[PDB]
Image (cartoon, chains in turn orange, brown):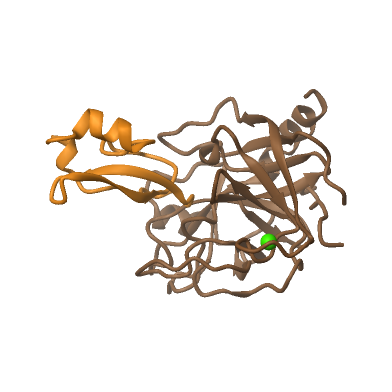
Length: 56
Length: 222
Ligand SMILES: [Ca+2]
């Protein structure tokens, strides 16, 4: 389950704010994404995040 | 920029901030209407901010101009990061002391050349701390040999390493797309690295000298 994976910033040096599902907190939170090599627990909005991972 | 110093208000006039509701990448002004940055910084709704020093408060020397076009290199590879370059056309031309363009290189720079890297990225290797003002760093271009030893099978002919093997001085999250200026010419674009300021893990940059022809022609036909 990719929804249980910790957020992955990656090697690129951008500061792009994305969302990831935090199973512990039971909600989607923001994190800094570097711009490349995103894993699946990386969403552009909280709504996408909840729709895909909510309740995982 | 980790381990750098405060540049000084508008001392790096070609430095721009790419804003999408917040600063997410840097870029270099190479023409009154064109900006060069990294392909991974591609985003819709980009607003380019020029003449910036403190990115958090309006100080009066700013010019905010939205992008009318964003052209990522046709051969950019999101997996290998090869050809990590993009051109952004401004909706209107900037008014060029505080805002000026930087020259494209006539030729490639050699290992050992000292360059100025700048940006509003994270200033901590372990942690998070984004500055309000622009930070600067002087780092030397490293040999293709050591770069390839630091990142086995990851360095292409279009990339170069710069920095210090000891660590402590490097570009970091929020610096992507920014300039690496050597001898007054734009030689690189901040691109990637393993963490920030790590020992034996220098920053990797897009080698601008290999794209001068593509840039000039692309600018002229758009
Ligand atoms: Ca400002």
